[PDB]
Structure formats: structure tokens, C-alpha cells
Image (cartoon, coloured by chain):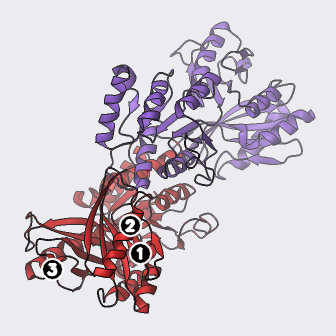
Chain colours: A purple, B red
């Protein structure tokens, strides 16, 4: 969402002024910028951020300028290469008192969603917002039923890191028509954890970085788990894999989008590791590398260790889509593709 | 193959000396280095290249040393993490008179395969070789039937850029047993051609580079097709896509592993382009970007232009595997995965 232009927006907010903020809420026909793309017009007229590829920037700028004057938020559809819904609002300390706290949450890696009414029959509702955390909600949409419905749905989207327009009836009845709410999620970068610092881990970590994951490579062997060997990994740790995973779980440093790749079949490490991983309250993906021989030998060993067929059903083994690729690069792509397929973008 | 250590090997060859060369011919249980990985021991004893991850390097070194002394080539199997077949031979001007010419072919981007007998009942055959081009073959395995069979199969592997052990009967009878021939292919980097220099082309070109392709980005629009916008593409050209493709075909600068991505649906460019691409004697992949609406509209337009259902069957549209991914990064991965799936590594 506003992460691109949040420093500039915050500085306006802190100074006491009003920014005009245009947020892309919905997109059709492959418009250039996605749900959450933001443009900010400072009181002195300076613009940052982008909502399109140039196509309607001038029009959004004028709208943002007009909206600051009237103080009335506006949903506008632009049609040109795509179709774009842009919601334009005045953001000040008066109109958005929580913005500083949200800036602070984004900085401290506390997940937070903002849910805004962008469409309603009663015009007084437009631009009302909820600030939603896991454990908390602030603000009011104007009705307990609306607050209840949106809070719930926003937390679900937040947990997934998703931003979307949800549609309700006027009192927040599900499947009703007439009220639309944009949920804009600010979740930290999801984690990819790679256990086994063999050379192939570098290829896995480059695909994880390409897909937007923060990648930790972890191996009990100091010679292997080295910054030099993995210079692009966000983090390289020397630990027993299962000790590291269990510690992340306990710290709440892993969430529902966390992705685990097991690149070892050393029984000393892989079984205790998968004993932990396969028992975690669900994380996005748990893959294990190996040929078909390694795969079946590992399954035998995991059954022998006490894993249930239901826990084993969580495991993607052998890892990746079967695309027929031979090289480490092809295998890395097959893994990234399976990860995407399992969550459905 | 020897590309890693070819400079060092060539310098030995040119000086009049004999190098001991160990080439990994076959691998099982995910051994660290693939078919073609080479180790070279210079007369002064200096080693470069690698056949394993450290596991049998000392043993291969001693074998290479012994093979230079006896002058007799040896196939050796090593079992440890994997299983490795390593073929060790003495390489000099006397024993391998074509090596200089092959160095020259690799440098000029002329595809060339070397086919060597690694196993035979008649020990005199071991280490005999054919040097195979598209249009030429030098050397003799010792029989017209063997030369005929291997030449044919080597050209097929060369055309695909593949290195493999092929198995024949003693006179080169297919499906026979007893004779094994390593074909080591030296083909240039395969090309990925990306037509449409939109921002998403960068993501496509990073995956192509990751997979080992040399990437050309091409667009008729000078503002778009720019080195600055695509700093990692090997090449960025301003041309009508169909004019560029047709010129590559005529020049023989595209081969059977060439991969084409069409990222435009501008009728001015895409139809003439696909008129050329879909009619080329087969190239590996021809994908076209678009939503389902764009896909069907483009097909209508291509039927209208005269494309046959058989030509249209060559087209991968909408592009990529359907993995459900939304971001440009996910789409890029889905495209790389479809490319791999279509060739089967």
C-alpha cells in the first residue's frame, strides 16, 4: 500500500497539514499499478507515488487537489490501458488520527490493516475506517454489524497479507450489495526458511528473494552456513534446524505465509526438523528435497518416528512441481512454482 | 563440459604437453557435479576443475596422473554422496589432434559435439572419438555402422544442447549392449527473445537469465526498448518484432532451443510477429501474454489473418502455467515453469 510514499505522507501528517491521497482500490484489464498503489499530493502541491503508468496521473492529481478543498472522499473509476478504481481522501491528523501509530506498526513489523468504506448508500459512511490488528480494532464504520463483519474479514486478509475490496449490504450483511470496503494490509515480508546450507540453497534463496520472501538459510555446520556462500540471503544462521524452527514458532516469528524448504536428508537433522514443522499450526508450505528413493526412505523414517498420515499430508515431497527439469536452476523454478500453486497467489 | 577449464587445457595442448582429463560421464544419487564436469591435471601437476564436491578428487587426480603415464584411458566408478562415472584420458596434440579446432568452434559459437567410446569389449576401441558438427563428422570409432549410429544420435543431442551416455551393441547396433559412448555437447547459450519492452519484460528476462538463456528484449518503441530500463538483458534492440525475428531466422541466429515471449497485444505488432514465429521450423516455445479476454481476442485476430489450427497449436496462450499467481514475479515464475515443462529439462 502506502509503503512507497509513507515517509512523505507521514511528514505531511506530522506537520499539521493535509495530504490528498489517491489509492488504487481495484484494477481491471491489467492496469499498470495494483490494489494499494498510492499517490500523495502535499499541501505545496508536490506529488509522489503512482497509480497508473502515466495514463490518469494528471486526473488523479486534480481530484486529490479538489478533495483536500472540499474535504469529501471520492471513489473514481478511470477507463482508458486498464480500468482503475481510485479512492481519494484527505489525510491529516484531524481526519486520520491513527496514521502515526500505523507508521509505527509498519516500522516495528506489527501487522496492521486499514479497512475503509469506499461505497455506500448513505454518503456519511464514505471514508469511515477501521484500523485492524490481530488482537485489536479501532474506529467505527457506523454500525456494530458492519464493524463485526469487516473486522473479521480484514483479519483474514491481513493474516494472508492480502488487500481487496469486500462487498456487503448496507448494514454489513454478507452477500448483500451496496457497501464496499477496501482492506489495505500492511504485513511484514513473508519468510522463507531454507534448512540445509548446500550449494543448491543459493538457487532456492534467489527464487525466494525474487518472489518477495525474506530468506533465512540455516545449517548446524559452520563451514556451510556462511555469509560468503550465501551473500544474498537476508540471514544465515548456524543452528540445529529443529531448534531454530521451534524457537521461531515460540517467538511468533513465523506466520501463516511462512515457507520451509528442507534440503537435507541427514536423519540426524531432517526427522527432528519435520517433527517440529509438520506439527506447527499451519504454515504455508513444507517441502523436502530428494529423488524418489530419498523421498520414500524419508517417509519410512518419519512413520517410524511417529508421524501421522495427516501430518505427512502437509509435506510436499519430492519438492517442487514435476516439470522434468534437471539443473539446480530448473529445480529451483519448480519449487517456486509449487509454492505459488499451493497458496494460489 | 570442458568450458570451465578449457583455457588451461588448451594452453597445455598448445605447448606440446599431455594433460590428464577426468570427465564426469554419468551421475547417480545426486552427485555434486553433472555429466561434463571436468578436472584437468597439467604436466607440472597443477589441477583445475572439479568432478565431485571434494569426495573423490584425490582419487581422480591419481588416476589422471597414472593415465598420462600408461597412455591408456579408463572409465572408473566412484561410490561414496552419489555414484559417479568418471572417464579419464590423456589429452595432447598427438592423442586429440582436433582439440584446437574445437576450442575455436566454442569461441566462434559453432555447435560441436565430441563422442567418445568409454566402454567396449574390444579394449582397442576405448577412447576413440568422433567430432560431430551439424554438417560434418571427423574421426572413426572403428566401424561404419558405429560411426553412422553415433553420428546421428550425437547431432540430435547437440541440437538440444544435451550431454549423455548412449548404449549400443559392439558394432553400434541399437538397443544392443556392451558399447557405451559419451556425447559431450558444446552448443552456445540458448536465446530467449522477449517482444514488448514493458516493465514486466524485466521480470521475464531475470528468469530467462536465471535459467541460462541469453535474453534479447525487442520493441519498436525507442523510449521503451532501452538499456537503462533493462540493464541485465544481454541485448536490447529497437525494431519491429516481426522484422527482427525474420532476420534472426534467415541468419540462422535462432535454433531449436530458442524461446519466444510475446508481451504485446498491439495488433500492429503481435499478428505479424506470430505470423513469422508460428511458421518457423520448430523452436522451443512461443508464448503470448494476456488475460483470457486478450487471449481469445488475439486468437480471433490470428484466425482472421490466416493462421491454421496446426500453427496455433504451437502457441502457449495465455502464457505460463496456471498457478494462480497475481504479481509480475509470480507470472514470471509461471512462465519459466511452462518453458521447462514443455522441453522436459
Q: Looking at the image, is mark 3 or mark 2 nearer the viewer?
A: 3
Say if residue B280 shows up in the picture: no
Q: Is residue B197 above or below residue A301?
A: below
Q: Of the numbered discs in the image, which one, if any, rests on residue B37?
A: 2
In the rendered structure, the residue with mark 1 lies on which chain? B
**Quadrant in the rendering for residue B50:** bottom left
Q: Is residue A317 above or below residue B150?
A: above
Q: What element does badge 3 sit on?
A: helix
Reading the image, the residue beneath label 1 is: B40
Q: Nearer the viewer, residue B195 or A102?
A: A102
Instruction: Using residue B121 as the reference point, say whether residue B91 is left or right of it.
Output: right
The answer to whether marks 3 and 1 sit on the same chain is yes
* Rendered location of residue A166, percent (x, y): 57, 24
Q: Looking at the image, is mark 2 or mark 1 nearer the viewer?
A: 1
Distance in Å between CA atoms under marks 3 and 1: 24 Å
Reading the image, the residue beneath label 3 is: B124
The answer to whether marks 3 and 2 sit on the same chain is yes
* Rendered location of residue B79, percent (x, y): 31, 54
* Rendered location of residue B334, percent (x, y): 43, 47
Q: Of the numbered discs in the image, which one, if any, rests on residue B241?
A: none
Q: Nearer the viewer, residue A61 or B310?
A: B310
- Find out whether the residues at labels 3 and 2 contact each other: C-beta distance under 8 Å: no
In the rendered structure, the residue with mark 3 lies on which chain? B
Q: Is residue A36 above or below residue B281?
A: above
Residue at the image point whose x is 44% and y is 45% from the top: B291
Mark 1 surroundings: few (<14), some (14-19) or many (≥20) residues within 10 A: many
| Residue reaching furthest to the top | A144
Distance in Å between CA atoms under marks 3 and 2: 25 Å
Q: What element does badge 1 sit on?
A: strand
| Residue reaching furthest to the right | A15
**Quadrant in the rendering for residue B310:** bottom left
Q: Which comes sooner in the sequence, label 3 or label 1?
A: 1
Amino acid at each position: 500500500g502506502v509503503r512507497d510514499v509513507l515517509g512523505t505522507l507521514s511528514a505531511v501528517w506530522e506537520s499539521g497539514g493535509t495530504a490528498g491521497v489517491g489509492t488504487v482500490v481495484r484494477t481491471f484489464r491489467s492496469a499498470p499499478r495494483p490494489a494499494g498503489a498510492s499517490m500523495v499530493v502535499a499541501p505545496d502541491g508536490t506529488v509522489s507515488g503512482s497509480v497508473s503508468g502515466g495514463c490518469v496521473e494528471g486526473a488523479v492529481y486534480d481530484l486529490a487537489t479538489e478533495v483536500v478543498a472540499t474535504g469529501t472522499p471520492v471513489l473514481q473509476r478511470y477507463g482508458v490501458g486498464g480500468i482503475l478504481d481510485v479512492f481519494v481522501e484527505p489525510v491529516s491528523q484531524k481526519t486520520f488520527p491513527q496514521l502515526g501509530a500505523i507508521r509505527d506498526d509498519i516500522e516495528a513489523q506489527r501487522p496492521v490493516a486499514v479497512a475503509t468504506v469506499i461505497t455506500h448508500p448513505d454518503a456519511q459512511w464514505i471514508g469511515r475506517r477501521l484500523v485492524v490488528h490481530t488482537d485489536e480494532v479501532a474506529g467505527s464504520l457506523g454500525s456494530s454489524r458492519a464493524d463485526a463483519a469487516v473486522t473479521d474479514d480484514a483479519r483474514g486478509l491481513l493474516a494472508a497479507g492480502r488487500s481487496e475490496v469486500l462487498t456487503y449490504g448496507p448494514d454489513g450483511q454478507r452477500r448483500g450489495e451496496g457497501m464496499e470496503v477496501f482492506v489495505s494490509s500492511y504485513a511484514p515480508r513473508p519468510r522463507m526458511l531454507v534448512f540445509g546450507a548446500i550449494d543448491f540453497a543459493a538457487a532456492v534463496a534467489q527464487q525466494g528473494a525474487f518472489l518477495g520472501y525474506r530468506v533465512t538459510v540455516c545449517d548446524a555446520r559452520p563451514v556451510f552456513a556462511t555469509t560468503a556462500r550465501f551473500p544474498t540471503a537476508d540471514e544465515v544462521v548456524v543452528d540445529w534446524p529443529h531448534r531454530y524452527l521451534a524457537a521461531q514458532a515460540e517467538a511468533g516469528a513465523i506466520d501463516a505465509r511462512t515457507v520451509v524448504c528442507v534440503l537435507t536428508h541427514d536423519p540426524k537433522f531432517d526427522v527432528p526438523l519435520l517433527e517440529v514443522a509438520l506439527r506447527l499450526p499451519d504454515i504455508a508450505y513444507i517441502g523436502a528435497m530428494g529423488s524418489r528413493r530419498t523421498h520414500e526412505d524419508r517417509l519410512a523414517r518419519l512413520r517410524e518416528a511417529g508421524l501421522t498420515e495427516e501430518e505427512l499430508a502437509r509435506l510436499s515431497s519430492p519438492i517442487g512441481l514435476d516439470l522434468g527439469g534437471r539443473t539446480p536452476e530448473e529445480t529451483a523454478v519448480s519449487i517456486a512454482a509449487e509454492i505459488i500453486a499451493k497458496r494460489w497467489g
